[PDB]
Amino acid sequence: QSRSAKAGLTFPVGRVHRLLRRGNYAQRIGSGAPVYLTAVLEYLAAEILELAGNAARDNKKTR
DNA sequence: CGCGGGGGACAGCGCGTACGTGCGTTTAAGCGGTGCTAGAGCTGTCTACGACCAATTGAGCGGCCTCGGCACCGGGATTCTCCAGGGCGGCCGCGGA
Image (cartoon, rainbow, N blue to C red):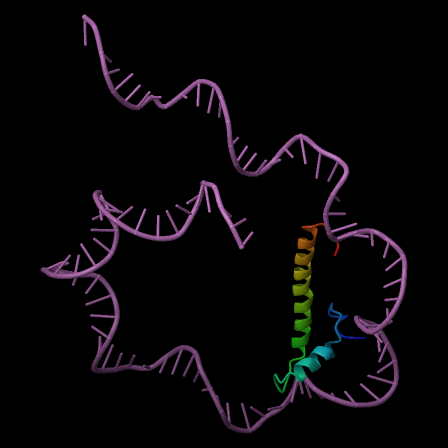
């Protein structure tokens, strides 16, 4: 079971950890940084998706 | 591509005042000094704290297909605006005694 589920997320956090690791950022990557990134995705995508739905109900379109 | 035209771009000149420049006299900074002490900082350190692959694993995806929604006119007073008479801002002028 991925560690995102116990933290309130869904990610396989190792995927983002690999992305940062192969991204030529730093030799040591903090373990909590990908988790905070996943939380940032969750909430920023929440507010942006609610903006998208806001403008969708502005035209009564379900898509 | 073409034309009517009319609201809008562009200019000429007066207003006048709004900065602009020349008079004195400041309020507060620059510099010399200082005596400290208060923050910035690497060295023994040592530990905890991150990385990666075995057993599993779940989890989101790869692919289709239903169906409650997309697109907009039948269906249409009102909105949005445009244009012709009426009473009027009155304005104004001119003349008997």
